[PDB]
Image (cartoon, rainbow over all chains, first blue to last red; front, top):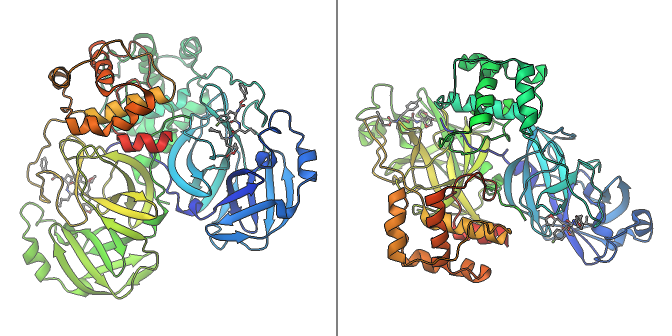
Length: 305
Length: 301
Ligand SMILES: *[C@H]([C@H](C[C@@H]1CCCO1)NC(=O)[C@H](CC(C)C)NC(=O)[C@H](Cc1ccc(F)cc1)NC(=O)OCc1ccccc1)[C@H]1CCOC1=O
Ligand SMILES: CC(C)C[C@H](NC(=O)[C@H](Cc1ccc(F)cc1)NC(=O)OCc1ccccc1)C(=O)N[C@@H](C[C@@H]1CCCO1)C[C@H]1CCOC1=O
């Protein structure tokens, strides 16, 4: 038993991280097959980051302007192109450690593991959620751009995130591996702010089921609620509305524990109005929303990768 | 910026995990060089779990009684021995993925990463602390024995934990890689319970410094305290006593932030007295104690 914020094993991704340098800017790249992916702002100088014209900067750069280092071996760049906010560097050698992989774009509320890297070397791994406002609450220092987020399904690595920037509140924004930003942000050092963040209701409910599975059931009650009545309350607390799809997804946990979803919603509604009243749930004094229903089933059933 | 419960990248350990089967028991083993380490209770029968005589049980086994599988390849066992509560299986092949590694025994309050495995395959990685009562608050299901805890420094893996058992409160107990249990626990299914769990005070203080480093100062106050007065108060909340050694260890963070250690102690006293009053610290509504001073410096710098 027990329940932890658990990341995917990172070995398959560690073997793909390299160091990319252009001029004085050094960050991380993702080496898959014979291509290295990294943020396009690697070609910017400290002064070109305010109003960059990426077309112009890239046109003026050459293959040899890019220094790629895989460990202590330097990869020869034989081509370069841009796709949205990601730079693609062709190298003359395929990564022998390339795993089975896909590029996937995730939606708000879904979770993934972040491999934080510096100078092409992985330093740590942690589990994150894509917030409803399309930011992630990560832990990144300078030089961490190009760090990637991923999931593992069967033996296939699904890359979903590449880190680009930090917003004034200390939250983080990035792109998918095709260079499309998550959220309404741009890779420029102009004033930007994320919209109001809301709570991922369906994940909170999944985590309450994990709490029950692990023996925490003090917060339950005999009452139920309608989806309409619950959503009226949730919207007043900056909670995401719960849809019928969300309820269906919690079916497995609803059956395993014998607690109807709308019964748990009544528990959550009461928890929102009254609070936790000095008690904790699974060792937390807050309502945790960075576990999806699948995450709960995955951890409570010992799925391996 | 930001602050998260961050584990070490697990690749170096993933390459060492194998499956070990003896009789009907299947669990995880750690394949380093030409030796596989696993809990000795893999040799127990369903009837031998209360008062096993492991010496006697092992004498009766032969090399071919142990089935070791690295992926889809079976490793030939050519020898076996016991070191305390850990079984050592000599195989005819050195693991080509063996990293630079050490065996270390950690002290309560120290943190490490756990690679949870089943049938020799990793399922997840998470960060843990050795509690003052010598348990860990992990996430483990049946079949997880042999999962290991570790740190990585430079490119050297320091193995510090191997999982053996779960105690009635849902907490977990295991050994170092020399087979010596942390705490007074034994690999027998006789009644055992962990002592009262306390809060790792020095780690809470490090985490408050991390909050300041990250721009949060709402919990500070104008007061200071003596070390003795702090410990008299803290122990009333089931907090571990803070020693002068702990104070010395917080020196670097005190200097970086300009906040004396005993001034931060005064802040903690008030937080225990008042609670958070609807506020959070580094995204938590509780005082977190699973970050060491070393962890804070590494993540924030
Ligand atoms: C990585 C780096 C990652 C970032 C640093 C701390 C953790 O995440 N990315 C940047 O620095 C990025 C680069 C521009 C997009 C080209 N810019 C920002 O993150 C800045 C804020 C920042 C700058 C320096 C830092 F050390 C930390 C944070 N974002 C920004 O300006 O936001 C818009 C805004 C402007 C003014 C007022 C309000 C809001 C890569 C950068 C260079 O090398 C890397 O590895
Ligand atoms: C040989 C034993 C060391 C094996 C070990 N006993 C235990 O834990 C048991 C509890 C238990 C949990 C779940 C189970 F299903 C079976 C048993 N403790 C215990 O008697 O306390 C003492 C005590 C006794 C009376 C009252 C109070 C405390 C054991 O079951 N270890 C497994 C790891 C556990 C499972 C969940 C996380 O930790 C994995 C091993 C077993 C065989 O193959 C494996 O992989």
